[PDB]
Amino acid sequence: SGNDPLEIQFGAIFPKETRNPSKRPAPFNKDTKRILIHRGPAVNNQVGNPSAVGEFPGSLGAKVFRLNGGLPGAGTSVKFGESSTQALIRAAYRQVFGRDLYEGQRLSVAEIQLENGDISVREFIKRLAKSELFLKLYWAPHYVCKAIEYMHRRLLGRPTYGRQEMNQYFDIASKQGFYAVVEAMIDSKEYSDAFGEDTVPYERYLTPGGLQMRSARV
Amino acid sequence: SIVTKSIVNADAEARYLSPGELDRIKAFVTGGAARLRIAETLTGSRETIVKQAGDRLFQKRPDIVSPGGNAYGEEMTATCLRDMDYYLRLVTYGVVSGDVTPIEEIGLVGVREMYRSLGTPIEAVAQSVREMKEVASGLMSSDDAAEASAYFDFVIGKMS
Amino acid sequence: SIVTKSIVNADAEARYLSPGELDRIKAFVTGGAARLRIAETLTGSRETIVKQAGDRLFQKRPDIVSPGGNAYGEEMTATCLRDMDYYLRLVTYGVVSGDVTPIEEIGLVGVREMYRSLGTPIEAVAQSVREMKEVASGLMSSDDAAEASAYFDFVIGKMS
Amino acid sequence: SIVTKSIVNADAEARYLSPGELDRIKAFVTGGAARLRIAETLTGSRETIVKQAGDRLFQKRPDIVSPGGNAYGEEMTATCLRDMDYYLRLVTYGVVSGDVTPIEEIGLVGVREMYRSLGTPIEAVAQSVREMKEVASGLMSSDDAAEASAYFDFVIGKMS
Amino acid sequence: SIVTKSIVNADAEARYLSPGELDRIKAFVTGGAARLRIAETLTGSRETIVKQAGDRLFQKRPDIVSPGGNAYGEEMTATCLRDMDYYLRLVTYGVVSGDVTPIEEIGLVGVREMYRSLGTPIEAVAQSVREMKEVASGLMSSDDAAEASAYFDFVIGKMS
Amino acid sequence: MQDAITAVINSADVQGKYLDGAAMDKLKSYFASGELRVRAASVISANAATIVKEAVAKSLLYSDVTRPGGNMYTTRRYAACIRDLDYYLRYATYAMLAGDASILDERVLNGLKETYNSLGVPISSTVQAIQAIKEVTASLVGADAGKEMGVYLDYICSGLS
Amino acid sequence: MQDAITAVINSADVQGKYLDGAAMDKLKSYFASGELRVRAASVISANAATIVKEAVAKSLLYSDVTRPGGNMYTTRRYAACIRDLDYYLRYATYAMLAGDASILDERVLNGLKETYNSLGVPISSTVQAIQAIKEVTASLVGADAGKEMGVYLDYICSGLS
Amino acid sequence: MQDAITAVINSADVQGKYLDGAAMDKLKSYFASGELRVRAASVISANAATIVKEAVAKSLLYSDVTRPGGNMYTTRRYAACIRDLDYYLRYATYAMLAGDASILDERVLNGLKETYNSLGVPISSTVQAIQAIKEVTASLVGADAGKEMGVYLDYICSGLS
Amino acid sequence: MQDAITAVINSADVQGKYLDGAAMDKLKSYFASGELRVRAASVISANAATIVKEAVAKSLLYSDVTRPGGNMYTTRRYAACIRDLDYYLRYATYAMLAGDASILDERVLNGLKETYNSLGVPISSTVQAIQAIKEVTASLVGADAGKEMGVYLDYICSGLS
Amino acid sequence: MRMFRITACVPSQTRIRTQRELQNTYFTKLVPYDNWFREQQRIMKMGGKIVKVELATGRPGTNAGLA
Ligand SMILES: *[C@H](C)[C@H]1/C(=C/c2[nH]c(/C=C3N=C(/C=C4\NC(=O)C(CC)=C4C)C(C)=C\3CCC(=O)O)c(CCC(=O)O)c2C)NC(=O)[C@@H]1C
Ligand SMILES: *[C@H](C)[C@H]1/C(=C/c2[nH]c(/C=C3N=C(/C=C4\NC(=O)C(CC)=C4C)C(C)=C\3CCC(=O)O)c(CCC(=O)O)c2C)NC(=O)[C@@H]1C
Ligand SMILES: *[C@H](C)[C@H]1/C(=C/c2[nH]c(/C=C3N=C(/C=C4\NC(=O)C(CC)=C4C)C(C)=C\3CCC(=O)O)c(CCC(=O)O)c2C)NC(=O)[C@@H]1C
Ligand SMILES: *[C@H](C)[C@H]1/C(=C/c2[nH]c(/C=C3N=C(/C=C4\NC(=O)C(CC)=C4C)C(C)=C\3CCC(=O)O)c(CCC(=O)O)c2C)NC(=O)[C@@H]1C
Ligand SMILES: *[C@H](C)[C@H]1/C(=C/c2[nH]c(/C=C3N=C(/C=C4\NC(=O)C(CC)=C4C)C(C)=C\3CCC(=O)O)c(CCC(=O)O)c2C)NC(=O)[C@@H]1C
Ligand SMILES: *[C@H](C)[C@H]1/C(=C/c2[nH]c(/C=C3N=C(/C=C4\NC(=O)C(CC)=C4C)C(C)=C\3CCC(=O)O)c(CCC(=O)O)c2C)NC(=O)[C@@H]1C
Ligand SMILES: *[C@H](C)[C@H]1/C(=C/c2[nH]c(/C=C3N=C(/C=C4\NC(=O)C(CC)=C4C)C(C)=C\3CCC(=O)O)c(CCC(=O)O)c2C)NC(=O)[C@@H]1C
Ligand SMILES: *[C@H](C)[C@H]1/C(=C/c2[nH]c(/C=C3N=C(/C=C4\NC(=O)C(CC)=C4C)C(C)=C\3CCC(=O)O)c(CCC(=O)O)c2C)NC(=O)[C@@H]1C
Ligand SMILES: *[C@H](C)[C@H]1/C(=C/c2[nH]c(/C=C3N=C(/C=C4\NC(=O)C(CC)=C4C)C(C)=C\3CCC(=O)O)c(CCC(=O)O)c2C)NC(=O)[C@@H]1C
């Protein structure tokens, strides 16, 4: 249970093993699969409808940011393509880090290299995830598997299903390190299916506990 | 609702509502009388709308109400008219809200799965909504009919 | 403009402009003359607006025109008033277009960065625009004043 | 076409085919002869299958071939029979390949959109393919009838 | 080099370089004399270092020179001593750099796969670099021995 | 999230009912309040930074909270706290526009108390800061829209204590 | 993208002057024609599906394009072609409602020819289909709106040319 | 990627043709060859590492490709070359299983030539090493399956050369 | 990127030789320059924002470039320009501190001139502003350190020019 | 770091998308060298058509000084 963070907008909040001890060990073998609740139409859950992966959830799920419109300079002022691209950049920051950064923290080179068509949205979020700021905020201060779990939620928009995903990312962490774990998550097939080269990741699934936290209040 | 749509867009953008969105909300709230009048008209004459549209549907698609048809018999036909009533009520929700979201969330997400399970022909459900749209448009001014037609068409297209 | 903004909002969901958007564009086109005159009122009295607002600001923020300030001396006072005139021009563009975008895309994207490089305090630029707003509002009717105040306040909000 | 699926699934992990997959491929290869016999039975009797299925459809759905319908007229009935023959050809492709993949890739991706743009009732095409299945199953043993019915019913499940 | 990695780490955070990095650049530049002293000592004494290391390795690992070993015979012994000389080259390249990067770019990024494709036991190569270490650590002064031992130990750890 | 219109529709739909006189009365009342809500929200969007600034200066500055050892001490923690105040003000404005507190429960108050308890963020000081925001907003926007904004800011406070 | 309003504002700002009388006249020009633009947009919005249907009927069907070996042959190809024509109709509606073809350059032609050449989509037959769409739209909307839509559809064709 | 079966299906479909006698003969030929195809693919699976270990020694080691200045001298390049040859073996095996080089066009020869040109990897040497792998595979697979694997490896080489 | 140390290492490894007499000499020259290199790096880092600020003030401001029509007009164009100059200073300082310009190729001039041609940023005013930057820098550090900075900033300018 | 500048055309199988998809179809993008093998495989196995690959940043024949 300690490896489940709060499903809040931003922050990696885990129960601390020693502070108000609450540990609830359970024997999950290597093959269990965690039941997740889709943020959208229930029938679009990829368990029952694996080809639904990437189907945008509409009003039942989160807002989805896409670089659908053209990028500026793909001279003249009042070019309308400046608001959409910047809204997407700030959305990507809010997705990878949970919230917007303070002044001076944004990866400006990556932003211009994205706004100039030199990279894709996927490449930019990879740069954000591999940034030293992400390492300091979300990788370094945590148990390795807590860091991986929070990473998975931010990048794939869902908690991990079980020991298969967890073990592969954890093994990469053992062998290669943080950048390689980020690479594995963003280069995985499911990322490509759910998010192309032009979609900012978003919350796609919740645990029962997170949904209950959100929807059980008076 | 338009208010919910604008708030969701702003929240996902981590900003306050833009002046355009605030002006859209103003235009929606100040035009509330027309929407509520359209809803009143649809609610008051719901029985005749459903009855006439059901008769037109049955005459146009006799198979669904004849032996072997999904709606054959008294009970199944009554259930068919009840489904039509459900959708007219949902359309009232949509016209009052100024937004098709209540209709979509209450009666169109997974509708094909449900009607395929039941064996109902979805094309006929769409045609029944078409009949109800025609009958309802008959009972109000052209402006009001044009207003409610967008929601009727949303429902029809989601089944077509 | 409102038409361009509506076009992008419609294309964001891959559809046609809704009847609500089209009717809002209709109302904007028909009310065109009122804003085509509000822009003229702001334009014809531009020098009065800029200079009266600048005097009111230097009464509000005497430090900037004082030695060590960003605007001390006649030269920098004149260039600060130059910026005031620029932003009044953008506000006139905004009232004409019906949208806050050309203001944003001309004078508020990276404004903090540029003025950081130059040393200007930004709360004081917001105050300059606010004084321009007050002086302009005093020159026109209450409803016209509110219509222009929407855009003046947008500029104020994007500065402090 | 389990060879393609097995290779694609093996290329996912950048590995070679495991003994189970290779045994599956070999068993599929052996079944090839029976699959070819079924395919040739459907192919040789293409004309009668299509003719009888079309005749049966035109009695269950007489509206289509009467004035105002889609397939009305010798030309449009000819195109309708051509569509039925196309889908029979795709079914033969499926039985030989052992998979519905060619059927999807040639006939069932965007079929609803195509026929809606053409105005063709999709349920009527589904009934026509069901009649083709009935006639064809009238010429095959139980095993072969079930084997071809897999593909016929998949076409029916995607067409409506 | 240490300078290259300082620069790339800085450019990762888009900064001009922090005081500790420049302090280390100063220290390494000033100690260039000692580092080049060690490098020249190893270059001039390379053949003896390799010979003694190989003799003590083979006394430690008499299997690789036995039949079936990767380095069996005299030609394969020549190839193995050549690899020992190559990694001594890389040690001298590293010491003058102040960083391990050249050693990884040339000799360690891919070494495991190379030796497996060759059948060489890479742990025996680790032992060879060890024997090189305990020979070189008596051929030069006490501090120079450790200054080279850093790179010897890095190679050993990266080959373990 | 639900606004006032959607709340009415949900109650009706859960009954399976068409909208009767009382539901239409609720809709009419909300439409009547819409203009006031929009004016107030525009004012808050205009003066959000000032509202937060004045609430902080009123409630938190020049106290142990900002001094070494307090939770707002250090520029990082200062920035995080004023960011949180901006979040709360933005969500209170959302709620006021919608006329429904549901967005607060689904987006803000879910797990917030556990968050602040795990972080060691003092709750009473945060509540005082939010109440200062309420007073500043009341003095800025009026006494009616001030009252509605107060309802939703007090809702945020209720979910934190 | 751009429209007539944005066009005049851009000219003025690049020059560096408040909107002068001539600019106001050029604005009034777009203002006066607004009714026709909105009307044509709404009509074509109502009839877009039928417009595409009729255009494909009299431009592509029963030719080597829809037969085996033609790039409309399979179901996927036919539906994709209908999707492309839907794009052309709605983007020409977008441009007509604005008075400028900037959006046509932004979100339609930005790499279109490379995509067709790589995927083998024909240029002659898609140009013919676009011109058939022009014919059908001109019939439905009227004379002036038909001419404007035709101008923007010609823009798309020439971009493909 | 398409197999021989799907290749024949597409050949008949582009003509809108049923599977004629020649197509049936091709399908029967592939079904007959399936036994030896699967046998060879099983034998390669246990010798791919050995095959590459021997082919590289036969064609690459102790030349100006692995000495200083040759494009294998660094361990990075040696391991990368081993990876390229590993993938060549496995993809030739896939193509042999499918009885069609279509996959070798999609997942092997899609931008490979321009990737090697950008890095100065010698096309001559990689062609020679692929030929060596073909020779080695011939000894452990057999004669006819040897011809199959040689045809597919030669197809790759002609793609590069 | 390569430093002088890595440049000589790369040459020796390409030719497959130990550190030779000329290699020792060139390493020694870098070691003899690596005190003014670090001092200039520290001084440039100390006051880089002022360097760019004064350069822009004396070389770009209050001319047609910043006026309506020039390519610096707009709060956004100005921001883009000042960050471009700031990046130029950072990467030129890296280049100076390493005794090489490969970093300028690999992290600045990767398609910069083509981008400016596409986007219309002048190729003369950029070099003029960089002249101002190198002037202020050289006047801020020294004759030889300034000479190095001017050499590398001219390398950037030539890559642009 | 070595950076390729890859141009590719990605077709759309299994779905007729109605939103704007041209940006995903024919694209030119910078790819780090280390990710280019994986990316080449991903574009290919997706059905893409990699028109062009170049070495935008870096040199051939470089044994050291690549990062
Ligand atoms: C039907 C007999 C009863 C019923 C069902 C119902 N379920 C949901 C939603 C979900 N159902 C599941 C269940 C599973 N997902 C899995 O992966 C597995 C393991 C194989 C199971 C059993 C889940 C996870 C959901 C959430 C959405 C999702 O599918 O991801 C609903 C909808 C609830 C809602 O409020 O939308 C319903 C209605 N309800 C009844 O009343 C029946 C008795
Ligand atoms: C006056 C309200 C405040 C103030 C302003 C101030 N600004 C400058 C210098 C510049 N201001 C700009 C701004 C713009 N140029 C544009 O094109 C746009 C879009 C319309 C904007 C907003 C620029 C570019 C400059 C540089 C000089 C130039 O215009 O060529 C100064 C002078 C600074 C100096 O050192 O000379 C001043 C004083 N300063 C205050 O204190 C007021 C609060
Ligand atoms: C002096 C060079 C400049 C200046 C200073 C100034 N600051 C304040 C108020 C505060 N300053 C801080 C700063 C910090 N708190 C921290 O924890 C850290 C790091 C440890 C810093 C740097 C804070 C928190 C405050 C708020 C008051 C409080 O401490 O509780 C003021 C007063 C502002 C007011 O209106 O009260 C002033 C004057 N002002 C200048 O003009 C100089 C350039
Ligand atoms: C300000 C009045 C008080 C205060 C605040 C404070 N908060 C934090 C840190 C965090 N705040 C949050 C809050 C939220 N996350 C959400 O998703 C939501 C809804 C959108 C909320 C409100 C979180 C998660 C954190 C931790 C992560 C992060 O800060 O980014 C701090 C800093 C604590 C630290 O050092 O980590 C502070 C200072 N502190 C006071 O003293 C005031 C009373
Ligand atoms: C018969 C059971 C039903 C019917 C058929 C019908 N179809 C059309 C027109 C077309 N049909 C197709 C379909 C395909 N083309 C292909 O290549 C394949 C995949 C192998 C298929 C399935 C196409 C493309 C057309 C367009 C015409 C053309 O080919 O040029 C018609 C004519 C419609 C009209 O008005 O022109 C008809 C009648 N109609 C029914 O009512 C039956 C349910
Ligand atoms: C129809 C008149 C002709 C025709 C069409 C056809 N198009 C494709 C494939 C694509 N078409 C586009 C075009 C666009 N996508 C966009 O988002 C926009 C900009 C708003 C445009 C203009 C694209 C990008 C593709 C590929 C990606 C995709 O389809 O999703 C095909 C090829 C089908 C295939 O899969 O090979 C076809 C058939 N072909 C004809 O012969 C007609 C003349
Ligand atoms: C000696 C301690 C061990 C040993 C060595 C050995 N190596 C080979 C063959 C090769 N070794 C290399 C070496 C390198 N490749 C690089 O990239 C670098 C980095 C600078 C080095 C050092 C290479 C390239 C080869 C291939 C042959 C060639 O160069 O042409 C052998 C021969 C293997 C065989 O049988 O072919 C041997 C014996 N073997 C041991 O058992 C020792 C532990
Ligand atoms: C070995 C026989 C020869 C050799 C190889 C070599 N290749 C590279 C670099 C790359 N090779 C590939 C591989 C592929 N691209 C494809 O499309 C396919 C289909 C699966 C394959 C196998 C790639 C992608 C690269 C570049 C990116 C990368 O490696 O991730 C090198 C390295 C060159 C360099 O480091 O600059 C080498 C050494 N070289 C020889 O001399 C042999 C003859
Ligand atoms: C300032 C002296 C001049 C000036 C600058 C200017 N540049 C742009 C746009 C871009 N500049 C870059 C910069 C770089 N590309 C690289 O690879 C590197 C290495 C990090 C740099 C520094 C890029 C990528 C762009 C395009 C994308 C982007 O927006 O960043 C502009 C913007 C022009 C416009 O918005 O249309 C400007 C203004 N302009 C002048 O007039 C000066 C002479």
Image (cartoon, coloured by chain):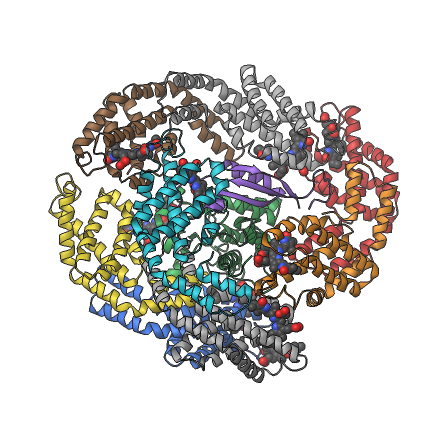
Chain colours: A green, B yellow, D brown, E red, F blue, G cyan, I orange, J purple
Q: Please state, as top left, top right, bottom left or bottom right, where the C terminus of chain F lies in the image.
A: bottom left
Residue E83 or residue D118, whichever sits in front: D118
Res. F79 image quadrant = bottom right
Residue G73, placed above or below residue I93? above
Q: Residue furthest left?
A: B74
- Can see residue F120? no
Spot occupied by residue J67 in the image (x, y as percentages of width and height): 68, 46
Indicate whether I66 appears above or below B79. Answer: below
Query: Residue placed at 70% from the left, 61% from the top?
Result: I129
Above or below D123: residue A150: below
Residue that appears at 45% across and 50% down: G104
Give the percent coordinates (x, y) of residue I46. 73, 65
**Horizontal and vertical percent position of residue B38:** 22, 63
Figure label count: 0
Using the image, determine if residue E17 lies above or below residue F47.
Answer: above
Which of B138/A11 is in front? B138
- Considering depth in this image, is F113 or G82 the residue closer to the camera? G82
Residue I15 locus on image (x, y percent): 79, 36
Left-right relation of F68 to G77:
right
Left or right, residue D101 beside residue E51:
left
Q: Quadrant of residue E130?
A: top right
Left or right relative to B122: residue I54: right
Q: Does residue G42 appear in the picture of this structure?
A: yes
Residue A110 vs residue I151: left or right? left
The quarter of the picture where residue I140 lies is: bottom right
